[PDB]
Amino acid sequence: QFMNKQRTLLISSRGVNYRHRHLIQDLSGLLPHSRKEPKLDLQQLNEIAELYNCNNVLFFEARKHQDLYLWLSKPPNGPTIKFYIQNLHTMDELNFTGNCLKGSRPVLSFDQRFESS
RNA sequence: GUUCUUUGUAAAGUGCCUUCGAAGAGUCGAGUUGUUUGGGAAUGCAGCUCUAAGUGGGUGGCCAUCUAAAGCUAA
Image 1 (cartoon, rainbow, N blue to C red):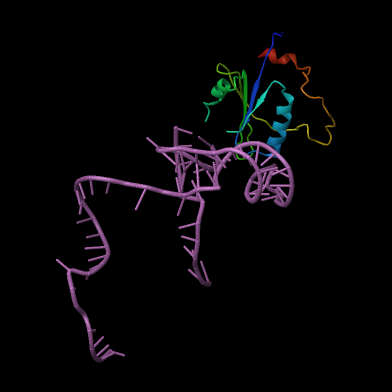
Image 2 (image 1 turned 120 degrees about the vertical axis):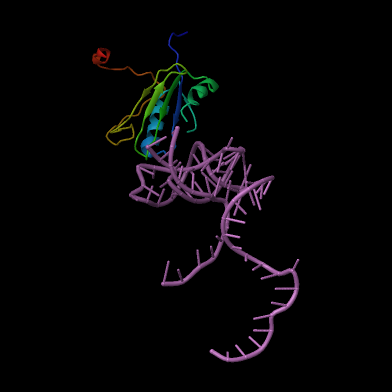
């Protein structure tokens, strides 16, 4: 079979938007190994990881229809990156032209600077 | 203002003490199709398939604030 196996739970908070909903569209369709769930304090998530039996968890917070915090972990052990997003450009813009076949596994470019911390 | 009628163990009020002490469901809410929103898009609504709780629930930053699903009301 395969060495690497993941599944990710997708749940955001209440007070959704088209910035939000556009994002859950993209990211939900981007993770073919992910499970997608209704939206919902801080405890129950790792337990939902027990119910749907999921090894990757993330969460989208909405404060005043502004603050989007992404909580990030792999339950129950995590650890978590609490996160905040700004200047969101989803896939849905006119100047992003793409049409992508579904479910693919990308290739990730990233900088070597990360390891510096 | 004058005058008549006041009635029956008739109401009501205030404080202290003792026993008690109910709070609105096809709703709320969930997914979705529309529709609108300057509110960022269901924000609000309508439809559909599903549909709760009682130291609860809503809304918002451990905390604060309020009590939905019934109703009247002059300037």
